[PDB]
Length: 223
DNA sequence: GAACACCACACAACACCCACACACCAGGTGT
DNA sequence: ACCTGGTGTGTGGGTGTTGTGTGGTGTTCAC
Ligand SMILES: [Ca+2]
Image (cartoon, rainbow, N blue to C red; front, side, top):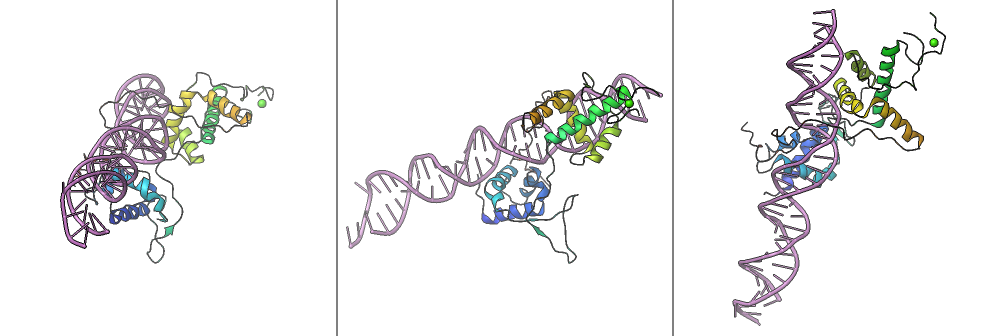
């Protein structure tokens, strides 16, 4: 083991203010390790998180793409506000938005009608299966790429792929109907609905070292 | 009543965890 | 020509194990 000097501590902080988006990463602290000999990505990251995060004070403002802003006179801008990190959490409002969107697509496909309307004649206005009562049941697609592109176009918080993998690994897991039924129920019971969690079923990949462990056992960059 | 070595832990250092956001691809079906 | 299941990957937010920087406790020293 090796002790952290104030020289190193203040150098960790100067990297983080210069790479704000990466504050919660593992790779960023693995990058500093290459500049502070005797210290690992793990140690550097725990050190920041535990004893140094509280001394952030300011960060430098960056762009969306997502480093780094300068004024007209080529100087850095000190900011007291964090920019988005790399990954965005899924919310209950987002999970419900997607369910409804898919329950709507599924409705548009199965009946060729589209709510809150009629047809996309005949045939008695209001006869339309509709909609609140319509249950997706066993249905899991087809969904064109058009869907998740348009959906992410309208709802920017998450990307096309981000959205599809939620629908895939979470929505289809819990059930399109079950989440609509759940979310609406919590609201009814004056409770605040929670995004669905703990549904990551993936077959065992032994081998493939645990991620988020940048140790002295590489480290060892040789670059 | 300063001064000098030996033995604790407690806390600091560094390891390791894992579910999932966001990602890209092959194979089947489609055509 | 495209839906869709298989699966890489490292983030976000922790937690587990372990080596060491001071302090606390106790003997072979001038005054
Ligand atoms: Ca009608």
